[PDB]
Length: 57
Length: 459
Ligand SMILES: CCCCCCCCCCCCCCCCC[C@@H](O)O[C@H](CO[C@H](O)CCCCCCCCCCCCCCC)COP(=O)(O)OCC[N+](C)(C)C
Ligand SMILES: CCCCCCCC/C=C\CCCCCCCC(=O)O[C@H](COC(=O)CCCCCCC/C=C/CCCCCCCC)COP(=O)(O)OCCN
Image (tube, rainbow over all chains, first blue to last red):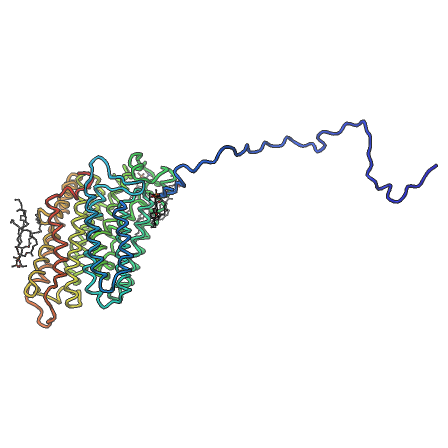
């Protein structure tokens, strides 16, 4: 009672039901380094301007 | 302070929009009015300076220099219009523009609160002077003179700039008030020695110090009359003023870093006074006399005492007036005879009596006759030097002798004796020339009545 698979059937992506637990860290990755914290707050004008040599603005 | 700066800036469109025959009148009248307005800066406080704003401030050291600059502009205009008559309208306006720009740069230089702004204006004064010398000088040497005037200055000032920015990286500021209040001693190290040299040598070149002075005879001789007047009367003092500002951060290093400069100043003062005794060119003699007086000013600033600072201020003002007058006196005879050889035109007292009187008064102030402010400054410096070391009198007194010896020598060579027979084109003195001499000499004499007004902050 064996039916030969039709053209296009053996190349299907199928689903598999397994009792094997899904691996957590398959790449064996280290802990990722913490990022630089953030930019936060409101933008205030520069204190006493550019503060270049003699420029008051 | 803008009440001085803005009218000076307005002088430019005024001369560029004036009628072809009205440029001199307008420029002279309005420069005189600007000088009258600037005369109000002489009201000084004592304790601290007049701080107009964050950018500009006035001191008892700055105010006489500012008044001298604003007063020198109309005299330069009066002295320039004779030999510039044949010039076109546009080139006359360009000459007046150079003079106005020079005054503007000097006025901003003497009042800048911050050392980089002072440095930028201090260098900016170079360009108009160079253009004046190399475009309106009479002889072929002027070009070479210009080069000497330029690279002597820059070779001194480029290190200073570096030092200045270095200072702002460590101190955090270059504002002169902050620099003075937060001043700290300099340790005894090679780095400190070279920073001291970078801070001092530009002003040394500007004085000029003996041995770095070769640009001055060339530049002052080859320049037109207004160029010589501004170079001797105001520009040299840019060195002195600068030193008086920058020595506040150089203690206690100056206690021993000043020995070579003191030796150079005293010996070269003797040397330049002696050079004046054997000089065939009349303008060269005046230039070397300026070198000797500035050497005395260098000694005063280097010994760092209140009496020496007061004497240096007084001598700077007095020498500015006297040297400008002497240059104008020599230029009158040059325009008569078209030669600067001192022995060509002799016995001029017979032909020009009032100009001979002007010559005599200028020679008297040159040799520091009491109670002129020339001698006030000289005597204060000599007393401070005597306190520094009693042997200095030996050199100082010697200088005095030689000074008189060459001053009267000039007077005797050009005014006395018999007139040269073949020179028959000596016309009577013009009212313009007599008025220029009077406008030089009368303020100098009036300053005797109120000497403190030129004695500086240490008074
Ligand atoms: C034409 C006119 C131009 C202007 C002239 C400007 C003059 C500038 C001269 C500077 C004066 C002094 C500079 C430095 C101070 C002392 C210099 C040295 O000779 O003193 C001895 C220094 O010891 C040795 O002599 C080292 C210096 C010798 C090497 C330098 C070469 C000098 C040869 C002359 C070169 C010409 C210079 C001018 C070129 C135009 C002191 O010994 P010591 O107390 O233990 O060390 C002090 C320094 N510490 C504290 C940092 C350690
Ligand atoms: C008309 C002719 C005038 C010629 C003037 C030439 C002399 C000018 C003075 C020296 C110029 C450069 C000096 C740099 C400015 C000083 C600022 C400073 O403090 O830097 C020093 C560094 O000093 C130097 O490196 C300068 C060394 C010299 C470099 C160039 C040599 C040129 C010839 C040297 C002798 C000539 C200078 C004097 C000449 C006198 C006038 C003839 C210390 O900084 P740090 O690196 O952080 O060190 C801190 C720990 N100690």
